[PDB]
Length: 92
Length: 72
Image (cartoon, rainbow over all chains, first blue to last red; front, side, top):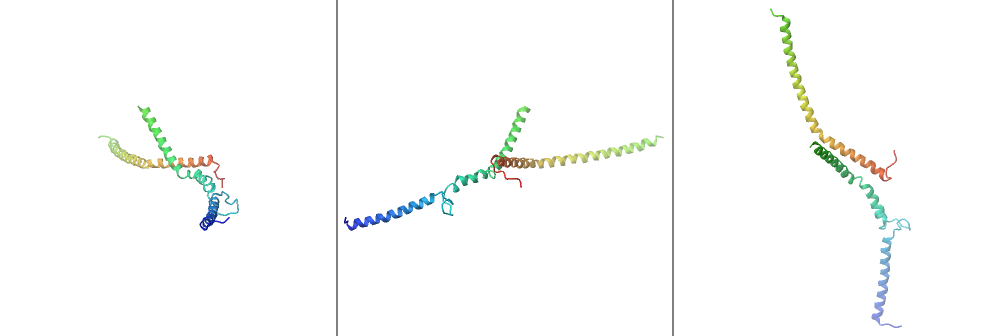
């Protein structure tokens, strides 16, 4: 099956294009592998160990640092407001 | 003519009145100092209340999740 030279150039360019196509597909997959330390590997690929399993692990205890201070201050303010409303309503 | 005891007792009574006056002055200044110190210290109730609230908060936060570490 003979072909014109331009067609053959188109064809082997298509071949090379398919080659780096599946190359890029493999790269994107390898990023998406949650196989971190499951398959033979020692680098973290974006997966729950970078996400909720990890960030949520941080978050279930970061509240003990940031939101708990507020909560305590708000609780004191709420108790003060309770005392104020009780005294104001009952005194009159 | 008058009994000297009466005069000496009047004198010592005058002294006792003066001493009671001095005691009253001292106690008044003491009350002023106590009022001032309590008024200035009023912030410490705030600080202690918030610290106690935070301590209770972290204690029950370690209770709620199973993240409470074992006693060293």
